[PDB]
Image 1 (spheres, rainbow, N blue to C red):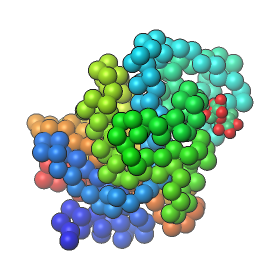
Image 2 (cartoon, rainbow, N blue to C red):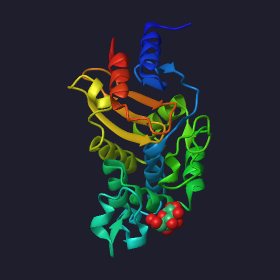
Image 3 (spheres, protein in one colour):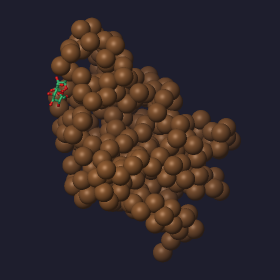
Image 4 (spheres, helix red, strand yellow):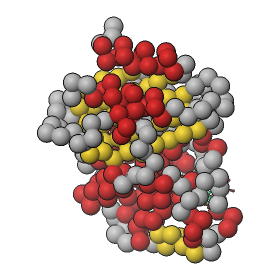
Length: 263
Ligand SMILES: OC[C@H]1O[C@@](CO)(O[C@H]2O[C@H](CO)[C@@H](O)[C@H](O)[C@H]2O)[C@@H](O)[C@@H]1O
């Protein structure tokens, strides 16, 4: 059976032609609202949260790790390098790389975080260490975005990503300074205006990370502080049947607007 929330999300999905996955956690009472919440979806750049968090975890026992400069060579650049291109033949610290990955969705920056963690499997291992049994990172940028229907590579479920984002930002999967740093980064994201944020009441504070990829995959994950009530975590994943489908950030905004009703 469905609730009216789920029915609205199903109708949005039907109209969009694609496949929508939603998970809301309301931390007032730790209830969840799910739509396809246990189905896998391609994460695309939403995986950058796990990678940044994994580096923050490393920094809990190496307090200057975040300030460590990393060389950016010409050959490091991939398909979308808005920050890293400014530093070719220079450096970016792991903090600068995290900020670029999270706040600009820089793919070179993500590949440096992945390298810091020893490869995609290092990101997955961090996920398992914080109780995320679902996340898997298989590939680097840009191939982690191929988003092929049903392919389990580089996927998670909405429920698992919401539980993890709660643990990382409101819980204590990270140390105190590190959790605050992740929240600061997410809150300052520059790429999210058309996605979840566009569907929320404007008085609400939010941190988010978007993703996009082939098959018109359009994603966003957010930690949200509504005005006068306990925070929320919201995941909205969306993917489409044809490889060259257009982005649909508006679907995410719509999903958020549905979920916000009654909150
Ligand atoms: O940023 C370079 C760094 O990224 C990794 C992946 O974490 O490799 C990616 O970038 C290379 C150079 O652009 C690509 O050849 C490679 O296929 C891609 O995965 C690291 O291996 C590398 O140190």
